[PDB]
Image (cartoon, grey):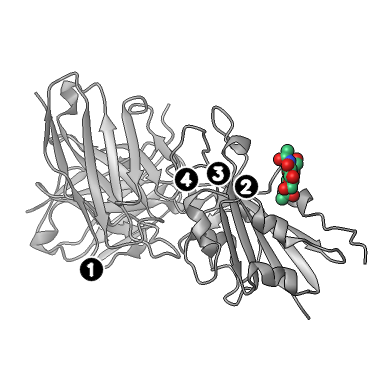
Amino acid sequence: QMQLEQSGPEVKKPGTSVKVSCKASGFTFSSAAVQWVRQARGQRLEWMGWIVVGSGNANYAQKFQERVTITRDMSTSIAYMELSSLRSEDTAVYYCAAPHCNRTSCLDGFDIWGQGTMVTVS
Amino acid sequence: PNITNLCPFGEVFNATRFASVYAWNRKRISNCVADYSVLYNSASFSTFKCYGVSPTKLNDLCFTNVYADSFVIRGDEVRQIAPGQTGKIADYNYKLPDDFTGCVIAWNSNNLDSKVGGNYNYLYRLFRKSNLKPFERDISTEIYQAGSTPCNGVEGFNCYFPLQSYGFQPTNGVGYQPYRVVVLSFELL
Amino acid sequence: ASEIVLTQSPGTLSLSPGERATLSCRASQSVSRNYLAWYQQKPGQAPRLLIYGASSRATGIPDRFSGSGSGTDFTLNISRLEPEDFAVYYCQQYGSSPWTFGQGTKVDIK
Ligand SMILES: *[C@@H]1O[C@H](CO)[C@@H](O[C@@H]2O[C@H](CO)[C@@H](O)[C@H](O)[C@H]2NC(C)=O)[C@H](O)[C@H]1NC(C)=O
């Protein structure tokens, strides 16, 4: 069994900040990497950033550079993302993607996919 | 006889700079008279463990050659300098034998190395293809590869840099403060 | 300007059951180390990995799915589309930052 389970719904007033978690189990999380994807209702997909777990070194798109914070916690094996200055455009569904790897190496592709957490801006 | 010609241990314990853990410094010691009683009974030490010889048995026995190994590591990782332990420092950086005959020493060096504003002088190795052999060493900084696909000379999705920095700061936690560790080995042939 | 912008050729595609079909996902430059992958999504569901490297097949993917590609040009083929195979498709490139998707493509039963 390999799984990536997310926290679930969040509802925030406009102008505030939101935080999301996803929890990983079933693989050597110390070697893998995580990628964050965001989806609006019938509006395709939007890549925003990627992080390497072993080092914490993160890279962000320019559009989401100043608004997105990506963090990991190895002792509990948790992925954290924080978005500030919420806009009406931010009513969407978020995904975190990661492969499965043994200690030695990785699958060279992303197959462990979460279920999706919805963030609503009232 | 009149005792003279003492060993240079002070040149090791008191020094200007200390090498990184993945490039641990090694010195040979021979043809000198050492006084381990001073080191054992000095009050400036925090972890003093000897394996194979008691502290007085150190003064009793004589050996052929001595090896001194020096590096610096963080607080919680001092536990890994002992036979039959696991951890990234032990597995990929520095490994002791399962029948070790020597002594392990570690003491806090908060003020010496944790300069204000953060430091970037010390590094440790994060990835490798195989476990380190006893006393094996490696300095090559080739781009680490995961996966079947070949890796170019550029970092990327499964191409990673095999070294990482310690973010030492004087305002850090109790266990993230620095520690200087010295390992002494005695061989009799 | 953006580094790489992807493009999926087919639009809304309608097929009789089991009719062979082909899709193409091309680009402006050559993706470094051949990083293109295909994902499959359904309404009210999360995507699943289909093919990585435009050639390799993932665990659980039947023999009826095939792909190929090189440089600027990649393609995907399905011969006998089961009724469960009709969903939305997406192609992604993760060679050099920033990684980007396509515009998607919908497959429906004729
Ligand atoms: C490192 O050098 C210091 C001197 O700079 C040594 O400290 C002296 O040690 C003797 C013997 O214990 C004491 O009588 C002195 O009072 C100490 N002086 C000071 C100023 O502390 C120290 O022993 C050296 N360390 C080692 C391991 O050789």
- Location of residue C2 in the rendering, given as x and y in whole percent from the top left corner: 41, 30
The residue that label 1 is drawn on is C60
Comparing marks 3 and 1, which lies closer to the viewer?
A: 3
- Seen from this angle, which residue lies furthest right? B1
Mark 1, Cα crowd under 10 Å, few <14 / some 14-19 / many 20+, is: few
State the quadrant of the C terminus of chain B. Answer: bottom right
Q: Secondary structure at mark 1?
A: loop
- Going by the numbered disc 2, the residue's amino acid type is Ser
Give the image quadrant in which the ligand numbered 1 is located.
top right
State the quadrant of the N terminus of chain B. Answer: bottom right
User: What is the spatial separation of the Cα atoms under label 3 and label 1, in whole angstroms?
Assistant: 49 Å
The residue that label 2 is drawn on is B44
- Is the same chain shared between marks 4 and 3? no
- Is the same chain shared between marks 2 and 3? yes
- Is the same chain shared between marks 4 and 1? yes
- Going by the numbered disc 1, the residue's amino acid type is Gly
